[PDB]
Image 1 (cartoon, rainbow over the protein chains, first blue to last red):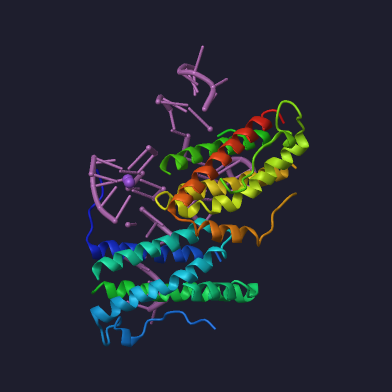
Image 2 (tube, rainbow over the protein chains, first blue to last red):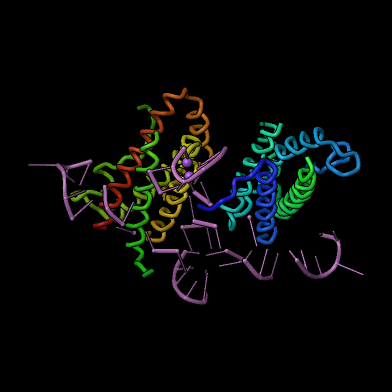
Length: 144
Length: 148
DNA sequence: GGCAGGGGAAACACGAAGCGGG
DNA sequence: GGCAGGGGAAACACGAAGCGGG
Ligand code: NA
Ligand code: NA
């Protein structure tokens, strides 16, 4: 019998690492107001805040789900992987909730009716803003 | 592993799907579901490879929107529904190479969005009869192909 | 649950190597 | 492509036993 039973932080930490790896295996296999961390949210060392930041992470991740749904009908060569980023994020959003809709429908169909040049631009910068957001989340969480 | 013919891939592709349905169906009237009839030509008499073949494709194209409806009907088996759905996508392609009637890409949604507005018993019934038809349909397709 | 939680892991100027059905 | 194609198989009245990443 082999697996060490983990605490909340370890579990959450491992999950983000799981997601960052996945995303990167989509970065290799490849108007916009995407969530970027701010100092007022209290996730950086300057003006740090364990309460305010956790709210920004859960709020943020939740706002990324639609843009993750977007990425699904975008990777016709890496389908299951792009799904595994979608579900792992959901999974992540549930680990961060222990510790503590048609606007989407419309803005999906806007992104999804742009030309390929625009759609691959959207893809590119979604993935990079997801990476930004996760890395700095892993960092903040490596404290509280 | 050893290699197989195009016909012996189709036969396995169906068998694979039929076992992924038996698994689904274990956990979980006014509709219009694809149903083999004498007119199709998939039976020992009144038989015809061409028409039978066409209807096997056609009927499987018709089923797709209903399998998409299945995804949410197995929240506690999301991948089993998905395998079944995408393993059917493949089957169609295989069949299409061995070769049509494709329903509108805008009428299938009105049905899908409506189905989802039924109370939880009608969904339960709708689910049990999607599987039943689809199984019987694939049961007949297999037998027919094991002849032509 | 169970064999067990909720189908399946140090070096480059700091940005490739290497543990599981119903 | 490669190691190969296009991420991963008898016995009950006819309806359980048990094979591989980029
Ligand atoms: Na398990
Ligand atoms: Na389980």
